[PDB]
Image (cartoon, coloured by chain):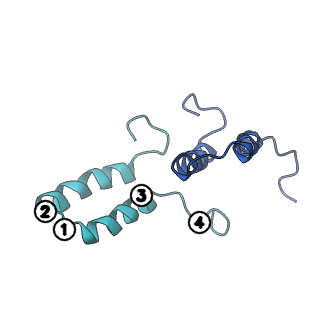
Chain colours: A cyan, B blue
Amino acid sequence: KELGLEKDDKDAIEEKFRERLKELVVPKHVMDVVDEELSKLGLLDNHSSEF
Amino acid sequence: KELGLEKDDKDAIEEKFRERLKELVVPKHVMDVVDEELSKLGLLDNHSSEF
């Protein structure tokens, strides 16, 4: 975990879409809406069907 | 040294999958899809129903 697998987070998915968001001027409407599901998705377990 | 045992993990399964893929030439599309899903499999528990 600390040395080998230093990954396992949505931050890869997140951050790649953020590379999109930089060019894609998202509306403030959607910068606000997105991060809520983002925070929920970060809370959720890797294996829940809800996740 | 603290693991021992055979590689009786999903990488056995990934390895049959990937040599499979080594013969047939996939589009990079399906390549990246199978790879990211492959890692997600590897995170998944060895016994979970979703696994």
**Residue B2 place in picture, x, y as percent:** 84, 57
Q: Decide: few, some or many residues near mark 3? Use Cα within 10 Å; few <14, some 14-19, many ≥20.
A: few
For disc 1, the marked residue is A25
Q: Are marks 4 and 2 on the same chain?
A: yes
Under mark 1, the amino acid is Val
Query: Toward which corner of the image does residue A5 lie, by quadrant?
Result: bottom right
Q: Are marks 1 and 2 on the same chain?
A: yes
Under mark 2, the amino acid is Pro
For disc 4, the marked residue is A6
Q: Decide: few, some or many residues near mark 2? Use Cα within 10 Å; few <14, some 14-19, many ≥20.
A: few
**Residue A41 place in picture, x, y as percent:** 36, 49
User: Distance of mark 4 from mark 1, alpha carbons?
Assistant: 31 Å
Tag in front: 1 or 3:
1
> Which residue is found at the position 19% from the left and 62% from the top?
A31
Q: Are marks 4 and 2 in contact (CB under 8 Å)?
A: no
Instruction: Identify the secondary structure beneath mark 2.
Output: loop
Q: Are marks 4 and 1 on the same chain?
A: yes
Tell me the subunit letter for badge 1: A
Q: Decide: few, some or many residues near mark 1? Use Cα within 10 Å; few <14, some 14-19, many ≥20.
A: few
Q: Decide: few, some or many residues near mark 4? Use Cα within 10 Å; few <14, some 14-19, many ≥20.
A: few
- Of callouts 4 and 1, which one flags the residue occurring earlier in the amino acid sequence? 4
Tell me the subunit letter for badge 2: A
Tag in front: 4 or 2:
2
For disc 2, the marked residue is A27
Tag in front: 3 or 4:
3
Q: Are marks 3 and 4 in contact (CB under 8 Å)?
A: no
